[PDB]
Image (cartoon, rainbow, N blue to C red; front, side, top):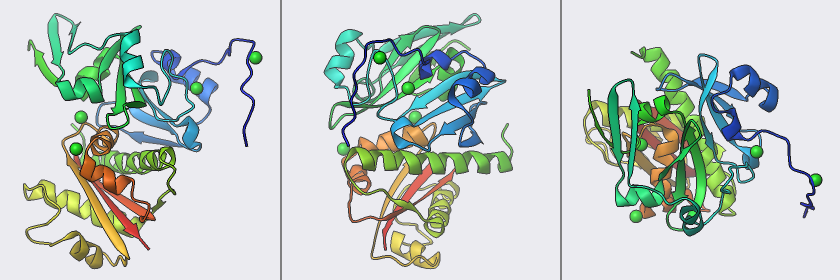
Length: 298
Ligand SMILES: [Cl-]
Ligand SMILES: [Cl-]
Ligand SMILES: [Cl-]
Ligand SMILES: [Cl-]
């Protein structure tokens, strides 16, 4: 199927960026009811629109105001850019800075981006806010856009920050569950982008992954091998998961699942698991800021 894209009139529909700063009633009117609503670790709730992977967007709502959004769908409008745009073309239209300065009240903040951050996830100012531009540095293409107001940027802290001067355990579990499903869906966006079959969610595998994330946090290590609970294979077997093949990606300390997954996409070893056509299933387990993907073939 090849559709005609002919156009003679400006499209009157609001963009994701146009929603930032507007109220939730406006978001509900323009976008409809989200698929899922789940808490974040930063005071906003995510309203997730994931039923069409080509249109994937999630909006963050705090006190009935839209404060952030993350765009992953290939067809979602992100002017002056487009999802898939080459880094050289993105830069040229608005050179990307290594330093970002802002103020709240009488305090001063200066983010210092590393050379890697400038190439993988630079920041550009937008009317009343910011856009974090997530790239796949191996293909040099724009793969996501995170819009944030000033308050959200300071909470997320995506880069090193120079400046002036309470979640319950059950809320934490809800936040972790959100990070797990976002990583899952956004991994399938990557699979689709790379012409690979999508992965099926496996709950028993996800439970194994959660246990690993918790073990790393509790026992102060970061490895595929648990000093007390063994290898990936040992863990999956213990969780009653049979498999023909397995793989694992681990991450720690990223702000959220979106950030962890972009770290994996931009690392050769982790990317190999994301792009392995042999895998059929995926369970994701998150415990605080420890994120684990367990991929399986069955
Ligand atoms: Cl038209
Ligand atoms: Cl759109
Ligand atoms: Cl991060
Ligand atoms: Cl690498």
